[PDB]
Image (spheres, rainbow, N blue to C red):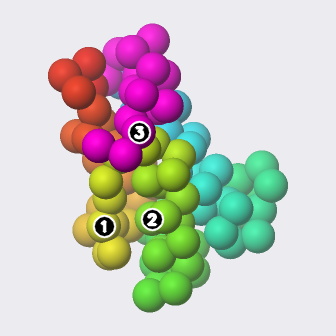
Amino acid sequence: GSTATLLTSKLAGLTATEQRAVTRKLVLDQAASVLGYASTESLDTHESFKDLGFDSLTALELRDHLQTATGLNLSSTLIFDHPTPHAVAEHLLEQIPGIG
């Protein structure tokens, strides 16, 4: 759906664990783009987007970022369903076709 092959071609090179790692960096990077960052400087993967400053605004463009980033289909309260970019990145594996 939509694309997937974009990021899916990434995870194809990883194992589920490294697939976590790569978008634990991507969701992070996106969240960074949202929040005002350029190197995920003020982010955490152990801390929830709540603390990152997301809400019914930034989470929306972040969620938007993840779907744009991955090509998969995420949701409105995505990062509030999955607390951390860690929980979200692994959530991005759930979207992945078998390889993930």
Q: Residue at x 37, y 52 (%)?
A: 88
The residue under label 3 is 3
Q: Residues within 10 Å of mark 1 (few under 14, many from 20)?
A: some
The residue under label 1 is 75
Tag 1 secondary structure: loop
Q: Position of residue 19 (x, y in %)?
A: 40, 27
Q: Quadrant of residue 36?
A: bottom right
Three-letter amino acid code at the position of disc 1: Ser
Quarter of the C terminus within the rendering: top left
Between the C-alphas of marks 3 and 2, the distance is 15 Å
Question: Would residue 79 be found to the left or right of residue 64 on screen?
Answer: left
Q: Position of residue 9 (x, y in %)?
A: 45, 20
Determine which of the numbered discs, if any, sits on residue 86 in the image. Answer: none
For marks 3 and 1, the one nearer the N-term is 3
Q: Is residue 81 above or below residue 20?
A: below
For marks 3 and 2, the one nearer the N-term is 3
Give the magenta-colored segment's residue range.
1-16
Q: Residue at x 57, y 41 (%)?
A: 25
